[PDB]
Image (cartoon, rainbow over the protein chains, first blue to last red):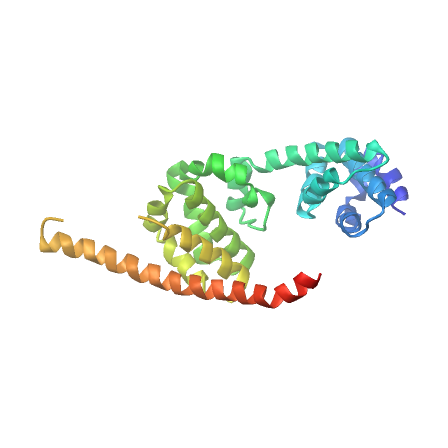
Length: 221
Length: 49
């Protein structure tokens, strides 16, 4: 069956049309769960065909994002340490790891981060867990008179969605973690109280990230 | 600070920080205990596995 999917994945026209069928989720589950090298190779070849052959950089980004969300990069890194009788497997792994690496670099843009905050799309987009982004860019949230922090705190005030809440708390935590001067800014926005409320939220995902955020806010003077 | 009034302003800050810290610390310790308890179930299973 996946050899048949791989034939469809070869043609740019079909790569654009077939998106509706949710292929990467299904094939990523098979790639993670199934052990056999045959299945592994033909999925990696299908994934390579999607990211090579797609008609749009946006369609490539849609596929690569879906792959990253479906933990494919973590699986590819394990598959790089696994070894095979056919080096086309390893070349497809390297190709995918590079194209997903570019997708992570695109996703790590502060403009994409800003756009997702402005759009309220706080849904574990891989940007939130990009250590490179936070380590090298957390100071940027001070832009336009602290506009992104005002959004994060406003989302912690306004939102019902536990994902939006847990993620906004996570972002406050990483902001402090990589920009310690920001603690005073979050206090000036009152945001310490929001995470101190949300550490008692009905969802453990919110509680956990809110606990981390308040703990970083409270870690030192 | 140099005066009772400025010391009172600093003390209001301290009283805020110390309460907040203890509230977080109580929940921090409680969460550590959940984490430890979950693992203290799991070690038996995981050791075998």
